[PDB]
Length: 236
Length: 236
Ligand code: HEM
Ligand code: HEM
Ligand SMILES: *[C@@H]1O[C@H](CO)[C@@H](O[C@@H]2O[C@H](CO)[C@@H](O[C@@H]3O[C@H](CO)[C@@H](O)[C@H](O)[C@@H]3O)[C@H](O)[C@H]2NC(C)=O)[C@H](O)[C@H]1NC(C)=O
Ligand SMILES: *[C@@H]1O[C@H](CO)[C@@H](O[C@@H]2O[C@H](CO)[C@@H](O[C@H]3O[C@H](CO)[C@@H](O)[C@H](O)[C@@H]3O)[C@H](O)[C@H]2NC(C)=O)[C@H](O)[C@H]1NC(C)=O
Ligand SMILES: *[C@@H]1O[C@H](CO)[C@@H](O[C@@H]2O[C@H](CO)[C@@H](O)[C@H](O)[C@H]2NC(C)=O)[C@H](O)[C@H]1NC(C)=O
Ligand SMILES: [Mg+2]
Ligand SMILES: [Mg+2]
Image 1 (cartoon, rainbow over the protein chains, first blue to last red):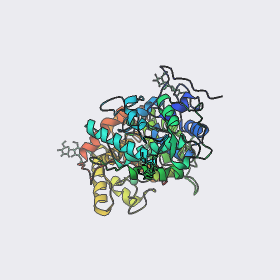
Image 2: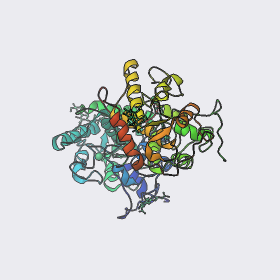
Image 3: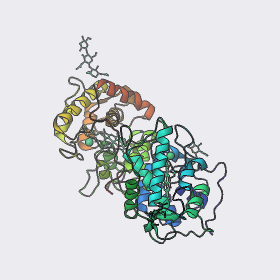
Image 4: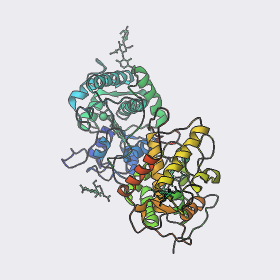
């Protein structure tokens, strides 16, 4: 145990991402959530989850745009709405109507109740969850943003939790609820529950067919202009 | 001084930006134009031009998206169309109809002929030049992309040449043609011609009103859907 879970203190920076928060809570990233570069993310995601540099370099550099520093962020910076952070999250509220940063059990209810009768979440349950979370945002949020880009990011995130928290073969696109629930609710690797780091590297080619299938099953259409413009920096 | 101009060799990476290419030609950045990080850009831009970290961090991190590396680029990477690189450049051709990378004297005619009768370029001539370059792209390039984002970037780039190549007070928003011409044609600081690095720091608050006036005077309107989506990575 060079990497025990410790609950974050009130001054440790944490963001809207359970993947990065969990790595910080285990000391793979700095426990203070500060001064985190793309090379640090690449190493931490590799050591923690066997996630490879292809997706971590791509996502990491987009995430860097959310801070004012030359080559690092604080995890909380990633909450910046419209860079990566988006409406119809699995476990956070939409920023126009709530808190887009912290885990929120009420929001998480959709995911937690999904795939009724099974002990795993899987590609079809993820797609249904996405459909129902988006419908919620569309019903309740007058400023909802829902575009090809946010839809792809959302499927990427579902594919992330299905593969990183799997019971050992991430190709299957399924993960025990008991692992995924601990991941979201505690931002802890569920080691005592029996989870282990994937022995298969999790790469863009591995994720891509999972992402596409989730989208396909999600009965999705875009909203409004459908323009994939992102926010390129914090307020100037 | 210690930073002499040398022409780039065949293997020295150079991009579509005369600002960075010039820094590399004088060794403020690596002469080979490779392994360049945002902290390197921030330091070279300060040393070479007295351009401050606010604008270099903001633009630098967007530029980092153009490579496949965790935290560096080669200068040539910045040619990636639709991240920063755009149609209706001052000195390059649009990618759909030509070479969007190298200096091009025929394209440069519009700038080189602007502000007739005067010895400087200034805010109104920069605006007229942007107008006419965009008009050329609208005429000749069926694939033209012209959005709020590309217009802002273009005005920023004109504000850059006016300020950085000024006769010593960047607030004036004017620059001797002799200096600006050497800057674009040779990617050389025009030292023997009489230019010296600004003693006034060039910052976002200094540039903003110059950028806005350039746009205001340019008689500009968006094209097509006006969606400011950028390309977030080179080919996956
Ligand atoms: C290391 C592997 C990673 C995993 C397993 C992971 C997992 C996830 C998951 C499951 C979500 C969805 C949370 C929700 O909808 O409630 C998410 C959200 C997010 N992730 Fe990651 N992530 C990882 C890496 C990254 C990286 C490298 C970045 C950027 C530097 C990033 C930035 C975000 C952001 C901004 C969100 C918020 C999107 C939203 O729900 O609005 N993540 N992540
Ligand atoms: C250091 C101060 C800088 C100066 C004085 C400067 C100046 C300029 C100028 C005048 C252009 C217009 C070229 C044309 O229209 O033909 C331009 C283009 C460009 N600059 Fe910079 N620049 C600077 C910094 C940067 C930085 C930090 C980046 C990002 C890493 C960047 C990326 C670009 C790109 C991609 C273009 C091509 C846009 C186009 O014309 O299509 N520049 N630069
Ligand atoms: C994700 O897991 C869910 C739940 O295990 C899978 O959905 C389930 O699929 C089974 C097999 O198709 C369904 O039962 C089959 O059900 C039919 C009639 O409903 C019955 O005639 C067959 O004898 C068999 O029992 C089941 O209804 C269905 N359950 C739910 C909750 O949807 C799903 O296939 C998995 N998805 C993936 C991509 O692995
Ligand atoms: C950018 O430089 C331009 C060229 O120097 C300049 O345009 C010029 O503005 C001058 C000054 O007002 C005008 O000069 C006029 O002065 C007499 C009276 O003293 C008038 O009766 C004449 O109309 C004469 O034009 C010029 O008209 C004009 N020259 C050119 C070639 O356009 C811009 O004002 C400068 N822009 C900025 C923002 O500084
Ligand atoms: C490491 O990150 C920390 C936290 O973001 C940085 O500390 C901040 O620095 C900014 C820049 O001035 C300050 O305005 C904040 O007030 C600081 N925050 C705290 C909590 O002290 C720090 O600069 C970074 N370290 C390095 C070497 O860049
Ligand atoms: Mg969100
Ligand atoms: Mg161009």
